[PDB]
Amino acid sequence: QFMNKQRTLLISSRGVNYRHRHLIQDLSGLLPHSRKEPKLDLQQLNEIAELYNCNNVLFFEARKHQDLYLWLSKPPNGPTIKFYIQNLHTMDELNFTGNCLKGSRPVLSFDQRFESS
RNA sequence: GUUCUUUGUAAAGUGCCUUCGAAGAGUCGAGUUGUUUGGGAAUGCAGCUCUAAGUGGGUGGCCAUCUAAAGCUAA
């Protein structure tokens, strides 16, 4: 079979938007190994990881229809990156032209600077 | 203002003490199709398939604030 196996739970908070909903569209369709769930304090998530039996968890917070915090972990052990997003450009813009076949596994470019911390 | 009628163990009020002490469901809410929103898009609504709780629930930053699903009301 395969060495690497993941599944990710997708749940955001209440007070959704088209910035939000556009994002859950993209990211939900981007993770073919992910499970997608209704939206919902801080405890129950790792337990939902027990119910749907999921090894990757993330969460989208909405404060005043502004603050989007992404909580990030792999339950129950995590650890978590609490996160905040700004200047969101989803896939849905006119100047992003793409049409992508579904479910693919990308290739990730990233900088070597990360390891510096 | 004058005058008549006041009635029956008739109401009501205030404080202290003792026993008690109910709070609105096809709703709320969930997914979705529309529709609108300057509110960022269901924000609000309508439809559909599903549909709760009682130291609860809503809304918002451990905390604060309020009590939905019934109703009247002059300037």
Image (cartoon, rainbow, N blue to C red):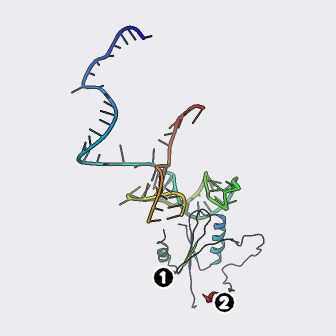
Task: Report how far apart the C-alphas of labels 1 and 2 lie in the structure.
Answer: 26 Å
Q: Provide residue A60's location: percent of width, then percent of height.
A: 58, 70
Judged from the image, the secondary structure of the residue bearing numbered disc 2 is helix
Q: Residues within 10 Å of mark 2 (few under 14, many from 20)?
A: few
Looking at the rendered structure, the kind of residue marked 2 is Gln
Q: Which numbered tag is attached to residue A103?
A: none
Looking at the picture, tell me which residue is in the foreground, A100 or B49: A100
Looking at the picture, tell me which residue is in the foreground, B32 or B1: B1
Looking at the rendered structure, the kind of residue marked 1 is Asn
Q: Identify the residue under disc 1.
A: A77
User: Which subunit holds the residue at mark 1?
Assistant: A
Marks 1 and 2: same chain? yes
Give me the residue at 68% from left, 84% from top.
Answer: A106
Looking at the picture, tell me which residue is in the foreground, B73 or B29: B73
Q: Identify the residue under disc 2.
A: A112
The C terminus of chain A - image quarter? bottom right
Q: In the drawing, does residue B29 fall left or right of residue B40?
A: left
Q: In the drawing, does residue B58 fall left or right of residue A27?
A: left
Q: Provide residue A97's location: percent of width, then percent of height.
A: 77, 74
Give me the residue at 67% from left, 82% from top.
Answer: A104
Q: Is residue B70 above or below residue B5?
A: below
Q: Residues within 10 Å of mark 1 (few under 14, many from 20)?
A: few
Give me the residue at 57% from left, 88% from top.
Answer: A4
